[PDB]
Amino acid sequence: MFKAVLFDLDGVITDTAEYHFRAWKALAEEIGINGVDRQFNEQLKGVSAEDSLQKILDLADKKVSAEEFKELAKRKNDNYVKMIQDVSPADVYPGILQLLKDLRSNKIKIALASASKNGPFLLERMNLTGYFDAIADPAEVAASKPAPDIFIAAAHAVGVAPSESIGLEDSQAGIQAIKDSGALPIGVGRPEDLGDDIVIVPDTSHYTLEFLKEVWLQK
Ligand SMILES: O=P(O)(O)OC[C@H]1O[C@@H](O)[C@H](O)[C@@H](O)[C@@H]1O
Ligand code: ALF
Ligand SMILES: [Mg+2]
Ligand code: NA
Ligand code: NA
Image (cartoon, rainbow, N blue to C red; front, side, top):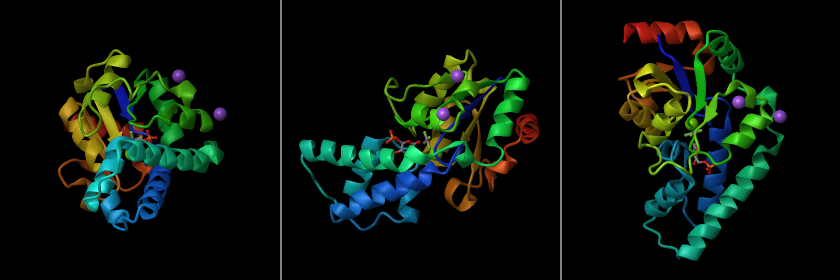
């Protein structure tokens, strides 16, 4: 049996992937870049703020100064942070609170494997902090998603090997990070976006302890 579950936050615990998208799209358009649509945004999910802005700039082969880059990242974060102030426990995605309670009851470790510097604040907004045994610090890893480091760190923070863990993700980059960590990925979203080579559920209500156990059993 698996010993830990390693959670992505945005798009897994709550619908904040939508808010990252809207904030990055708005930023892109302010600097005259119009290609940040939902399809392109599949390349932005899971990656750090710095990598997100770089991918957007790359889209238009645009070059900005280092000072401008810092200011643009800050502007997007400030906007995003305002957007999320009213997040509450009502915003936790279906099934997720039950899953956390069921994992806890069965002595399965719970760790956050989020790239987001806003992760601790969002878990507080949603009254979820008490369920997490550890939160991996995304500033402390040497390499961000799709590098596996954050998933490895999250497993190690709860005293479990990645190979004894399940990772839950909504992004291409995150799925790759889970694969390379040694943990077992279960994605949420569309196979058109996330692939046909791992288990994908259509919505978070499918993330039940019973389903996770069966996935684990089947390999
Ligand atoms: O800008 P933050 O809050 O540090 O978030 C970093 C990343 O966190 C990930 O969880 C999101 O999927 C990305 O979209 C986001 O860029
Ligand atoms: F959506 Al995440 F780390 F919370 F990639
Ligand atoms: Mg995500
Ligand atoms: Na709270
Ligand atoms: Na906690």
